[PDB]
Image 1: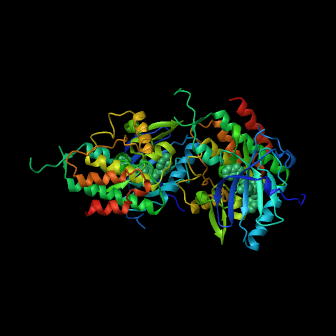
Image 2 (image 1 turned 45 degrees about the vertical axis):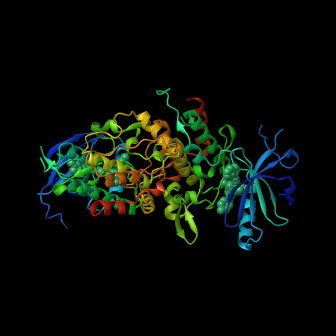
Length: 300
Length: 285
Ligand SMILES: CC(C)c1ccc(C(=O)Nc2cc(CN3CCN(C)CC3)cc(C(F)(F)F)c2)cc1C#Cc1cnc2cnccn12
Ligand SMILES: CC(C)c1ccc(C(=O)Nc2cc(CN3CCN(C)CC3)cc(C(F)(F)F)c2)cc1C#Cc1cnc2cnccn12
């Protein structure tokens, strides 16, 4: 990656999207960005971008994590993955710049919609083929990550972003959001794990693989067909979810699965169940999941 | 963990037929041996049920396994080593609270079976104590109503959750997606609009449940309003333009008790009373 800062002077401030312990997040406009970034430009208006601004008196520890995040993000270039557009690091304050997804994270997007009813034909609605199109984009992005030997480790709707025309980009917001605190279980010090999205081997042995990403995709797809109305295993405690992973290990018929979402076709629930195969090698690859869902989306 | 011995469950009568099993009333042969008569309710899964039904069965076991309170239904044991699968709870002889109150009339000493007003408050206090237990477990019931409360001897109440496995109360549920149905007449406005189920929305349902008890279960909430009008009414709570309607004061209900129900139906969830306060009011104040 070239060591050339994005020009701060090309970031017109529009709105503060969030504030946190070590800085703020701003929404900005960049006029005629073709000379600065290379993109599949969305439809002569300025390009919206998100900017995380590290606080100017950030600790060395915070700066180090900031730099490492830039490094991880710099290698990700795919239509269904969030894109690092640039950074400002040669002076304070440290800035990183991504593309902007106007509809926010996928959990809040689907929480505001209802499934369209064909035997009842007044908030916004979404069709079942469109839910399949969303899931197919997620699988497409995860497929790309798999080709990089990149294990996401925290796939869930809360880490998927929604742009125009239902475009989905996978992201990772860490633990910078109090909204989803209930989705994480504290194991050691400040480290937390999203156990309800994690495969049994992740919970019991800490084995995070592409195959465990497939397990998380099954839960994420479950969220999408639930329109994010309920936490996975919502009426079970964290300890009980951890027990459930031990029953996948025990393998004597006591493990439990997420139920088939209302109106979810049996074939799609069967796809989820293969993602939750006890043996990681029996879980479908993301290329198969993408192919299944992309065809199912067009044949529905 | 060892299973419950199947042979000790001696059959008395079938309490219900289900799409994936049956419910039996049973006597435990020798209750003193297993203590380390005695009637129990037993749900039998079909030996031909789908794996989905079996999965939903085991999850219900898990949920119920952690419920230990005098006013909550209690799982006594399970039979899961073989087919058919069985779960076992204590038995409440007087059925659910809706059928109990509907069979009674309010006692009037200044003038069928009767029930006093202090006993009605004792019933409602027991419900509030059980819900306080669930709240300490961060457990959101989501379907609180008299139809899900059971009556034993000495007017003891235990909260349960029968799902939608009874045709009796179909009118109390509104279909939203596939097989998913919602008890909108007991649901807070934020539940109907945004699907936000909290303990504070359980408090809203408690207000409606307390309305039921003081009505002696003679009328469905908003009975002359359609489901759509109830949903529209949720929208008027959101708008807060003064057009939202409330359940009327039950006949012979003191205005102070009705004022408590109104506080349970506050637009702001954070302004609704906690179950500990509702319990001490109904049991003492
Ligand atoms: C605020 C803006 C500038 C922003 C910054 C970063 C990210 C992001 O995802 N970094 C990421 C990091 C990492 C590796 N680690 C993950 C967690 N660990 C703790 C250390 C690092 C992996 C991956 C993934 F997943 F790609 F591999 C992505 C996203 C954004 C954004 C945004 C945005 C766009 N549109 C909206 C609308 N509303 C709100 C926010 N928006
Ligand atoms: C037939 C017997 C064996 C029986 C089984 C279960 C229950 C019960 O409630 N499980 C429950 C489940 C749940 C979570 N679920 C899982 C998901 N699901 C979609 C909704 C809820 C929550 C809770 C609560 F509320 F505690 F949190 C209670 C009750 C019984 C019984 C009985 C009984 C006793 N006495 C009589 C007299 N007549 C008829 C029946 N009787």
